[PDB]
Image (cartoon, rainbow over all chains, first blue to last red; front, side):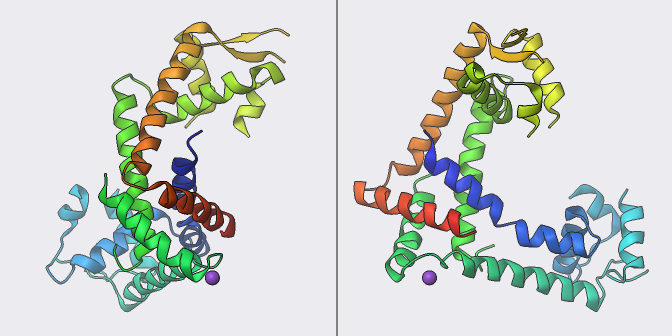
Length: 123
Length: 128
Ligand SMILES: [K+]
């Protein structure tokens, strides 16, 4: 009896499947991926260990250093391997996005975009 | 987040619905998983529900909590789980919250847009 909410939740959950599988193949968790992402995003501005505590973190950074994702040290920087990973995950999300229209006709593709915009605007 | 436009909107709408719902439930010291669980029990109890069927957040803890608060009981027909009247009243308040959230999805849409959205979302969900 709440079919729109059910479909929105379920599709929303499926948007994450490919990313979770890659994290697992790489031996990383969601906290590690996000941390690498956060550092990649903010390292030019400059980020220190305190900043990551407020947005252990010591042991995680050590794990990420051992995997060659983060530079050993003071500001924190991802290594090229870390930047490459962020790019990889972005591309995963692009492939998932492209899959949304797989089962849809041209008209359905346009209508979905128009309607989702309207729904999102209304709440 | 806006580099993947459909995904952006789907998650934005999802997160807005969930925030609406989590907040309206939280005031009642409830959460959506408890509501779903009680609802499932209420709907299927005459079929015979055991803890195993619910397994397939700690389920044992959540069931003990619902039982301690007087919402469900375990009856000797493995014991079967049933909603008590206080729990049936609570299912209805849960359901009404979910129904108002559902209606917020379609407020701004024509009947045709509602029909198109249902049809399309079924297809998208099937395809992945
Ligand atoms: K297609």
